[PDB]
Image 1 (cartoon, rainbow, N blue to C red):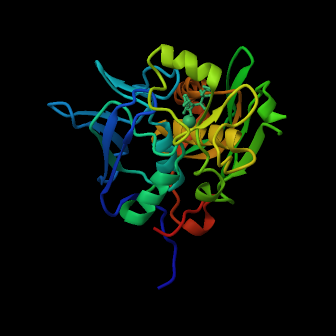
Image 2 (image 1 turned 30 degrees about the vertical axis):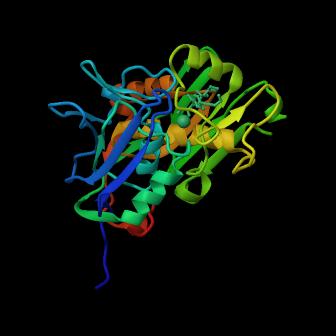
Length: 303
Ligand SMILES: CC(C)([C@H](NC(=O)c1ccc(C#CC#CCCO)cc1)C(=O)NO)S(=O)(=O)CC1COC1
Ligand SMILES: [Mg+2]
């Protein structure tokens, strides 16, 4: 028959298994993504510990936001969740358990591409409960110096980002806007790899960071050019990756957004400051569901 269909929560149809290396720790890590019940959200599970330590991927659990987005509970951390969370958000996955055998999510090829491929191969499962969205109803802005991150009301979901690197590799706009109620996360953004400049990578290594980085999982830039012999996947890959990171960091809200995000030189730390300010300002957002997908401002691929 023909009639209104609620937009439903989604989990995984099948389990996903992957093995990789942490970008910063260099450690080998085994990843298992599992389906989860309605209203679970995304939950990270350190299965190398006894007992297993579980950390919901929510803004309140964000520890340090230095080089990557890190979740903390007591003395236990899960590092670099942003790229996997970007894949979850981009495919509309509400509920899943993410089991990790080590403290850091594997970096894969530096983008969300391998995650979206593994998830879409396994397939998604719609669940018998309405999907909840957080709708921006007032402008919310956080700044620190010359960095800015803002939420604005928008009947859809749209992310804009601008970076301002003074570096010969950008002699480029350093700006991109993507409307995901219109274009596709998989198409526009998922394949954008992380990047680092050699000067900063050298410092990071001296601090026991970036230990797993290489041309196999990152765009590596020296003082003048990209060192990866096979080049860039997009002419604006750097700023597309900033958008990927933003989508992942924003999914620490625990629900998909109906609104617009605008980032100027933002990063994990300011992104999370923006989420904490939004959450505290309950006049600026509300939780909504859609009983008829045909009238909703957002749509999703077939599962
Ligand atoms: C883009 C970022 C937002 C971020 N990437 C990292 O932290 C990172 C660090 C090291 C490496 C590496 C390597 C190597 C090698 C072999 C040669 O020896 C890659 C990526 C991110 O994607 N977070 O999600 S960044 O902060 O701008 C990254 C700075 C550092 O310069 C710019
Ligand atoms: Mg990143």
